[PDB]
Amino acid sequence: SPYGPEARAELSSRLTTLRNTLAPATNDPRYLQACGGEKLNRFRDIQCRRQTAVRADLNANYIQVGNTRTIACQYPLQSQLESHFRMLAENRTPVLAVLASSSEIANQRFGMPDYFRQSGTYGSITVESKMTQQVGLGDGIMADMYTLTIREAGQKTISVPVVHVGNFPDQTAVSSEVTKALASLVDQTAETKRNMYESKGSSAVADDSKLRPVIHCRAGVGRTAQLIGAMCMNDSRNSQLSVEDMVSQMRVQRNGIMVQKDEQLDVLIKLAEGQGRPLLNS
Ligand code: VO4
């Protein structure tokens, strides 16, 4: 009963209603509008909740699912790179997880700058990329890791660990097993980096808005949301948080598309079932 087709249909029904309610109107007060002149949204129908927006010129949101705090964003546009790097630095980002594949990034029609595998200067910010480890996730899926060192006069220099799933199967969903392995890697990477900041006595440890994992694919609503859901299920503090809760929270805090595909919701359901975690509220 709890994970049967009836329960799953009811979950989908509730989530579909929510998506409709959250659909953006013209000049919607709930969503971030360009401020302005440059393109803000990579996709016109995939918008950034205003009240949880990280920066006025980025499509990026603070998200809290149960107790788990992250930032979900779109792949930054070329014009957004300086702002994106400043976001990463100010957040003392303990991990940046990029779920757009190498094939997607290499497709120049998609306008996705190769900002983390190359070094460069973006306005006042200079970034150095270094290759680190490579971790297999299962099914031949590989996480390539980097460190991004972000330098800017007047700012403390920040190094950001990057987890890039270079061969993400961008046509299809990754399995629950691969998702689990990825969530574990991303969480572990973040824990190691956060610990460094704690050991140095960083003031960012006491700030709700900082030390958040940053996760994006192309739009930051599909693969991104699947990973965030898996990360929240890894969090010891989230007992009894339902799948309905998780997805509703992602949607209200970013946009109604979070967990874009039924295929992605299937993975979250499987992970929840493995834990005896409820699908529905009440
Ligand atoms: O600006 V701090 O890395 O001392 O929180």
Image: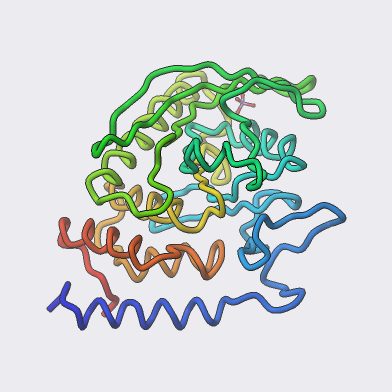
**Residue 174 image point, x, y percent:** 31, 49
* Image: 13 above or below 38: below
- Report whether 10 appears left or right of 87: left
Does residue 17 appear left or right of residue 126 in this picture?
Answer: left
| Residue in the image at 69% along x and 79% along y | 25
Disc tally is 0
Q: Position of residue 13 (x, y in %)?
A: 36, 83
State the residue lying farthest toward the right.
37
Q: Position of residue 9 (x, y in %)?
A: 28, 81
Residue pictured at 17% horizontal, 72% vertical = 3
| Quadrant of the snapshot with the C terminus | bottom left
Q: Position of residue 118 (x, y in %)?
A: 61, 22
Vertical position of residue 169 compared to residue 158: above or below: below
Q: Quadrant of the N terminus?
A: bottom left
Query: Taking 93 as reference, is 30 left or right?
Result: right
- Scheme by which the image is coloured: rainbow
**Closer to the camera in the image, 45 or 209:** 45
Taking depth in this image into account, of 130 and 232 the one nearest to the observer is 130
**Which residue reaches farthest left?**
1
Q: Is residue 231 above or below residue 157?
A: below
Residue 242 to residue 282: above or below: above
* Residue at 20% in and 83% down: 6
> Residue at horizontal 51%, vertical 47%?
217
Q: Give residue 117's quadrant in the image.
A: top right
Ligand 1 falls in quadrant: top right
